[PDB]
Image 1 (tube, rainbow, N blue to C red):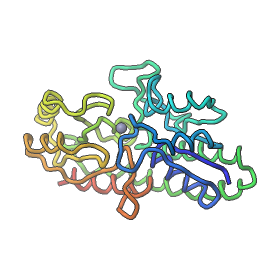
Image 2 (cartoon, rainbow, N blue to C red):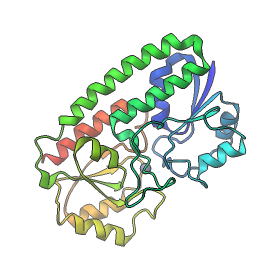
Image 3 (cartoon, helix red, strand yellow):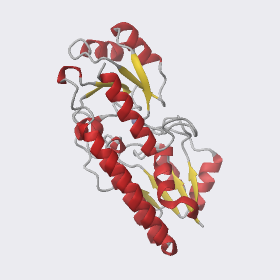
Length: 278
Ligand SMILES: [Zn+2]
């Protein structure tokens, strides 16, 4: 069987949807952990060196010049577009605020379901290239998975239609909602823009508190992969309740609602729309 390594649980889950029984799949970043900065364990280094295919997000999630995945593949003498593949290739890239330069991308493309489809098609193409005798399975599974994601994307495009503009604001700890905000017409705000920044100074909390006095949503949200303390402080100081945990940089643990890319996005759409409509 093809040996496949994925950098995190979101990419690994998309790969499972395409490949099912046919591959030997290893996922590096544990569920619930930050995928931006991680220290691979010896088993991760071994599996990466022995893999036939390595999938990573790209666009400044784990692949900055000094970032953990770049070091891993360079130490292993692996080559981009031969051994390892950025599943985000082909998306319309959004950058960090005020930026336009390579290396300053916003990585969170998968929160737009159109980009989840792009990721999945890229995964399927590279699995078919390296394991052509399972093409029938990969293509069949891809076609059904894409159809399912497209139906959810159509739902997402009208999910927030009944909510007034003066309370359409998704508030999370990390500024990970740019692609969702652009695709689905719901602006977003944050404590820290990206996880490599300082995660929750009193000044960052104060900046968000001041923003929430201008546009005041009925709910805040907190991601499954961050320390909740900063958002608990935002909630206490603003009086706006945390409505639900949501899934941004990780799927949920197995058996918990949201334990796949599809299920985490359905969860996010339901919980965010329900909380904002209060
Ligand atoms: Zn993130």
